[PDB]
Image 1 (spheres, rainbow over the protein chains, first blue to last red):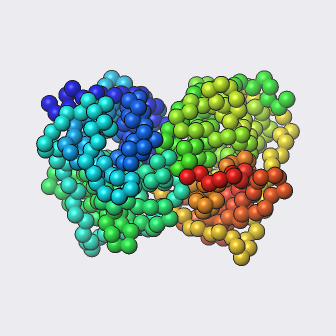
Image 2: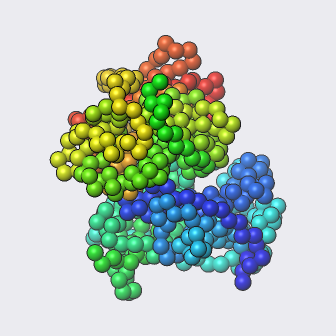
Image 3: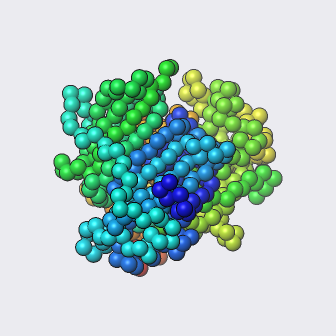
Length: 256
Length: 258
């Protein structure tokens, strides 16, 4: 199995009321927040701190997430977040995350693709082996492919809402927290849709960075699905018609 | 001392990167979030859950906050949140909170006023002693908390609109009071925020904000007589109706935080 011998770093996290939505379940923003928390803690423990990575003239940037949701963590549940830098090729790193309950049953499974961005030239460079080696990552030629989100196009029922990038959207690394894109994406859908649908799967592709003070336009299409008791939502986050993030979500329709 | 015999409930909390702003320090939203987390856990441990309080046709609604900030918790700091239902009178309940560091030194001190609002009629009902007795709160007068500045708009007032989001409505089907700080603090520009630290905060909640409403946040950056400080006077409204009035005291830093 790819990355079987890579380190599996884990930690426990109590899901707070403020990390949940009105149904008492953790939000997508929270799911990514805790996934990245485990990854940063693994990295810090190996001496791969944000300051140490930045001292090599580079920075890690996530390009894609593929999320399989069995059930979202509940309010006051102590979940286990496990993370693994499973693999890498010259330009891409493949990182996996597991969110499990106290018994170890899988709640969410996240796969991701990360690139190494040069702090000076602002372009993708080869992965510095000293910044991946500590994770015990498996070297590969072909990095695993994550399913691309639906290329967003306008429809007759397209929901559009503006959102301004706030000061609190910028986390300690001086860039916008990617997790906050879900605040905009999910809020585009009406409360009625959100209260009678559960998350099944999410495909995310980060295309262009959104910066402080910019106004993003979040677009959403509620589309039909071939799978029974399911619906698909196609989303786009853009600034001045430049595509920043594309997301496709598979939901399951609740009975009542 | 007001509420000496009242029970002291405490817990530890690890400040995460996502609970902090760009300077690696906890936001005001996080500060209130963890204070209220300590209060709900004290209440759950004593049997006073959100279900049994709501079974009596009533619910706690915070009307006021006075926050004394020595320093905000830092990213990855393990802070101790101590809480106490100090005292109460026929209508108002006085609740205190202490945010302390790993070595026991005080980071923040929060005082507050709470009232019981009916579920059906939506009026200020009398405090039921059964819902306060488990905290061991003394029956009292409750001193008046420091009032915010009465907001007056001027030619230089900073105004920004904010829309209430789905995630702003927390598990009890109401817009979480902590999220008001997202609007209040964001009204001020990053150039101000990056060279100012929190010293004090006063909050008055007049009217609750609901889902689908567009709030209008106002802010005046004012001079202060206190050495190395400035004052910001804030107002959150929903179509010519006061929702929240806030006054924040800040310490001007020698250099901006990169």
